[PDB]
Image: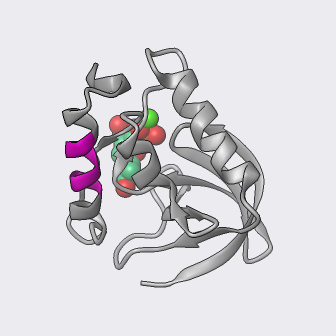
Amino acid sequence: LHKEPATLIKAIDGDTVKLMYKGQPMTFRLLLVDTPEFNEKYGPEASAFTKKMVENAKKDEVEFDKGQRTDKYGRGLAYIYADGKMVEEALVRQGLAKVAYVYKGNNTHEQLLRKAEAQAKKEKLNIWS
Ligand SMILES: Cc1cn([C@H]2C[C@H](OP(=O)(O)O)[C@@H](COP(=O)(O)O)O2)c(=O)[nH]c1=O
Ligand SMILES: [Ca+2]
């Protein structure tokens, strides 16, 4: 896999971000995680966490996996990095997202995220409290 440039257009919620990619605006849904919706417990805190990450970073990047690059809703499907930190791993490590939506062609970083989730679960963080 490889990282590609993108620029923040705007943070949306815990696991969706609008980015400019190859000069075109698109909504990206983070691969391999599920954050609560904003109206659910820990949703605002997830949305806040992701917003800070992607806004504060000097450099946001996208990384497609090996399978589908867009979902049925036209959202891009990628891992997102903020100054080289994977947004998925940060959220999961903090108990603000669960590993989820692990589909067969697009699961390169599953075990990294599962490891992070196990540590969050151990610490009883947020969603696991
Ligand atoms: C993360 C991800 C979600 N999706 C689809 C499955 C779910 O469809 P349904 O809407 O049909 O439940 C939906 C969940 O996204 P949200 O968690 O953003 O709602 O997005 C994929 O198709 N591929 C993926 O990699
Ligand atoms: Ca969600």
Q: Quadrant of ligand 2?
A: top left
User: Which residue is found at the position 56% from the left and 64% from the top?
Assistant: 81
Residue 104 at what x, y percent from top left?
20, 66
Relative to 115, say whether 60 is above or below.
Answer: below
123, 24: nearer the viewer: 123
- Could you tell whether 50 is left or right of 118 in the image? right
The C terminus, quarter of image = top left
Residue drawn where x is 61% and y is 80% of the image? 4
Q: Is residue 10 above or below residue 45?
A: below
Work out which residue is located at the far bottom of the displayed protein and give it. Answer: 2
Residue 114 appears left or right of 29? left
Residue at 43% from the left image edge and 53% from the top image edge = 88
Query: Residue 76: x percent and y percent?
Result: 54, 61
Residue 107 on the magenta segment: no
Magenta-drawn segment: 113-119
Residue 16 placement: quadrant = top right
> The N terminus lies in which quarter of the figure?
bottom left
Tell me which secondary structure the magenta stretch mostly adopts.
helix
At x 50% / y 73%, what residue is drawn? 63
